[PDB]
Length: 278
Length: 286
Ligand SMILES: Cc1nc(=O)c2cc(CN(C)c3ccc(C(=O)N[C@@H](CCC(=O)O)C(=O)O)s3)ccc2[nH]1
Ligand SMILES: Cc1nc(=O)c2cc(CN(C)c3ccc(C(=O)N[C@@H](CCC(=O)O)C(=O)O)s3)ccc2[nH]1
Ligand SMILES: O=c1ccn([C@H]2C[C@H](O)[C@@H](COP(=O)(O)O)O2)c(=O)[nH]1
Ligand SMILES: O=c1ccn([C@H]2C[C@H](O)[C@@H](COP(=O)(O)O)O2)c(=O)[nH]1
Image 1 (tube, each protein chain N blue to C red):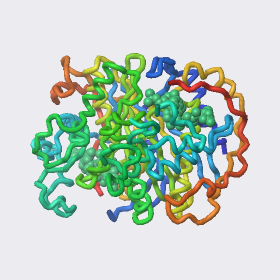
Image 2: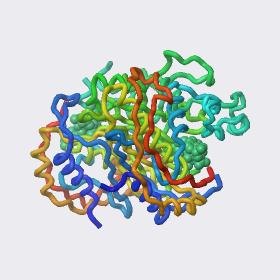
Image 3: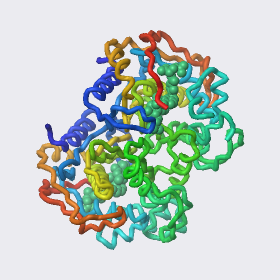
Image 4: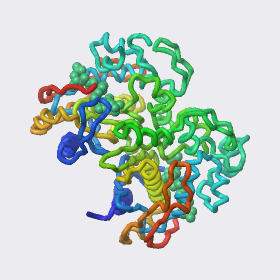
C-alpha cells in the first residue's frame, strides 16, 4: 500500500547518496545511476501525476495531442503557451525535424519539413498498436519506436523516449517505456504523465481499462545544481494521486481534445525552482 | 550479497505463482515489466549454473551477429542449430517468403546492427557501406564521448519487421560508462524465461566483455529489462525442478590476447574458467 510516488522519491534519494558524479553534454555535471524501473498503477481512474512538486499537466496533454496529430511544428505548441520545445527550435522556425509525431505516424518515410504531407508514407505505428490491441491482444510485438538511427541526425534533439510497448491481461492495458536519459528533477514527472495519459487514451478507444505504467530508465540522473531543491522536495510527503476520467465516448485515438480530460483532485505541493540544463 | 542468479530464479518463481495465464497453441504464464542486474566485474561471467547453458552457441551466435550475417547456414556449419527452426525453406515459404533461400533469416540482428536503414535483398548481398553501422558507432562514442546518453544500438526496425523470420526479441541496448567500467542495458520485448533468457543474458554479457576490451574499459553491469516475461505452461515441471537447485559460483571469462577491433574476435580468444553447472533440463520449444 506504499504510495507509488515513493518509487520516484527513493530513486532521487539513491542517486544523490550513491550515484556517479560525471560531466555531461550540457557542461553542468550530473550525478547518475544506470538502470532503474518503476511501476505506477493506472487502475480505477488513478492518474500518476506527481504531487511532491506541481507537474505541467496542460503541457503533458497538449504535447501528447500534438504527437498524435503527427505534428513536428513547435509553433503549434507555442501558440498554446507551451514552450517545452523552444530551446531546441531557433530550417524554418518551429520545424523540429522528424521527432516523435513523425516517427509515431510515418516511421521510415523521408523527412522534408513540418508542412510536408506525409500521408501514406512510413509506418503508422500508433494505429498499428491500436489495431493489434483490438485484434490480437496477446501479441508480444505491440511496440511504438521513436528511436530511428537513420533520422536521429536530422532531429532537433534525439528522443529520450526510445520506445514503448503495450500488454493486455485481466481486461487491462499496460504500457512500458524505455527512457534512455532521465532528468529526475525536471523531465521525469512530466514523462510519467505523458505515457500514463497515452495508455488512458489507447485503453479508452480499445475498450480496455488502464492497468500499469512501467517506467524503465537508462541514464537516470540529477543535475548537480538541483540537489538543494531536491533535498527540499524529499522532505515532502506524497498526496493521493488525482483521478482522470474521459468525459465522452471518444471513438478513435485522433478524436481526443484537451477538454475531454477531467483531472479531478490534483493537489500538489508548490512548484520548486530548478534551472534546466542546456 | 546474494548470488545474482537468484534474480532469475526468483522471477521464474514469481511468474509461475502470480503470472497471468493466457494463450502458437501453447499456454503462457506471463508478467509485464521486470529488471535484473548481473555484475560483470572482476572477470565474473553470468552464465547460469542451475542448468547447463550452451556457451559455444552463445559465443558463435554473437560473433555471427558482429559479422553482420543473417545466414543461419553459417551457424549450422559450426553445429549451432538455434536458428534452424526459423530458417528452413518450409518455414520461410509458410511465412510468405516464397523467394527466400534456406538459411536466410531476413534483416535480423547482424543486418540491423551493421546496416540499419539499408534495403534488404538477401543474406548474400554485399551491404558494405550501406545503412548505419550502429555497433561501430557505439564503440566510437564510448572511446570519444563516454558520458553521452545516446549510446544505443537498436534492432527494432518497423520498416523491416515484415521481412524478418522472427521480429527481434532484443529490441535495443544502451551502454553507460562510469569509473572506468562499461555497463549495458538490454530491452527485451519478449522473454521465454525457461529456454531463451539464460542464453540471452550470456549473449549481452559477452557483448559487453568484447566492447569493454576494445575500448580499454572494464565490464560493469548487465541490466536486463523485460517486457512480456513468460513461462510456457509445459516448462513448469522442469522449472520447478530447477528451482530446487542452488546456484554455484559463476565462471570467469578472460580474453586471451589484445584484440584491436570488435570485428577481430574469434571463439578461441575466450577462456571460460570454472563453469560447473547442474545438468540440462529438457524444455521443448513452443
Ligand atoms: C536538461 C533537460 N532536462 C529535461 O528534463 C528536459 C525536458 C525537456 C522537455 N520536457 C519534457 C519538459 C517538461 C517540462 C518542462 C519545463 O520546462 N517545465 C518547468 C516549467 C513549467 C512550464 O514550462 O510552464 C517545470 O514544470 O519544472 S520541459 C526539454 C529539455 C530538457 N532538458
Ligand atoms: C518460443 C521460442 N523461445 C525461445 O527462447 C527461442 C529462442 C531462439 C533462439 N535462441 C536464442 C536460442 C537459444 C537456445 C535455444 C535452444 O534451442 N536451446 C536448447 C538447448 C541448447 C542447445 O541447443 O544445445 C534447448 O533447450 O532446446 S534457441 C529461437 C526461437 C525461440 N522460440
Ligand atoms: O522528455 C524528456 C526530454 C529530455 N530529458 C532530459 C534528459 C537529459 O537530462 C536531457 C536530454 O539530454 P541528452 O540525454 O540528449 O544529452 O533532458 C528528459 O528527462 N525528458
Ligand atoms: O533470443 C530469443 C528469441 C526468442 N525468444 C522467445 C520469446 C518468445 O517466447 C518467442 C518469440 O515469440 P514472439 O514474442 O515474437 O511471439 O521466443 C527469446 O526469449 N529469446
